[PDB]
Amino acid sequence: GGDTIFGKIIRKEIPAKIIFEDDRCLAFHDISPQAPTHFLVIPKKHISQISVAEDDDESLLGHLMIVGKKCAADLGLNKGYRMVVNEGSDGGQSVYHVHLHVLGGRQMHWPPG
Amino acid sequence: RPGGDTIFGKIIRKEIPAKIIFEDDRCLAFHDISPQAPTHFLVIPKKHISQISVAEDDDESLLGHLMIVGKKCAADLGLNKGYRMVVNEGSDGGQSVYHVHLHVLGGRQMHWPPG
Image (cartoon, rainbow over all chains, first blue to last red; front, side, top):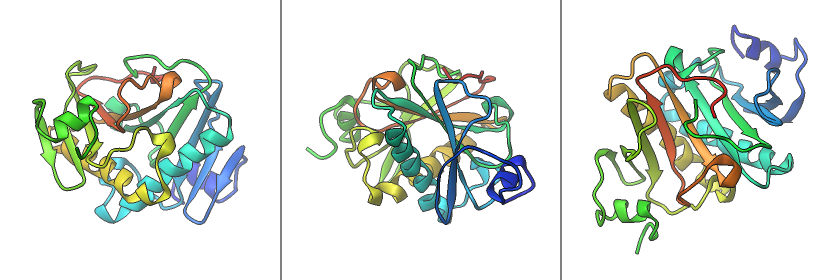
């Protein structure tokens, strides 16, 4: 799981509002939401940041996006939504465990930050 | 015509020019014509998928390949302080071209919320 708060969430050591879980990822609502619906999809494998993901991680990263879009449909986001991965300081990455943001329920604007 | 006839299908088939960063059998990376950051490029599959909400379960590897190519191109472009990847879905997501595309933006501090 890793040495971050997201590792604690994976290990069920602190609570989170879990939306979906399987053997390789976990989706849960963001504790500081930026849209009426704002959740995260994270791998259970501790990849600290997208910049260090290996080629063998391709299917896992794609799995996060497929889970993300299936959860978005399940949460009723039929008008659309935005998916975000942050990397590093300029990207605004807040936890050094790879995570996919999914935001919806309001108009998302341009530029995306 | 393989890839469809959105602007991105035309770019895939070299019918409309673009500033290409990387190309392989599965995807194409090229700079955005209206950049929202000092570096702003797109990674698209060559397979036509209109939007992420209709991607199939067996598109997992392809979607992940977009992100791996995105981060490898970011490194090759010297985005050593980081970057943001964005996929827009539908009207609320701000989608304007219905051929799946991953944005990669960097070269400045990105703000929160992401739009």
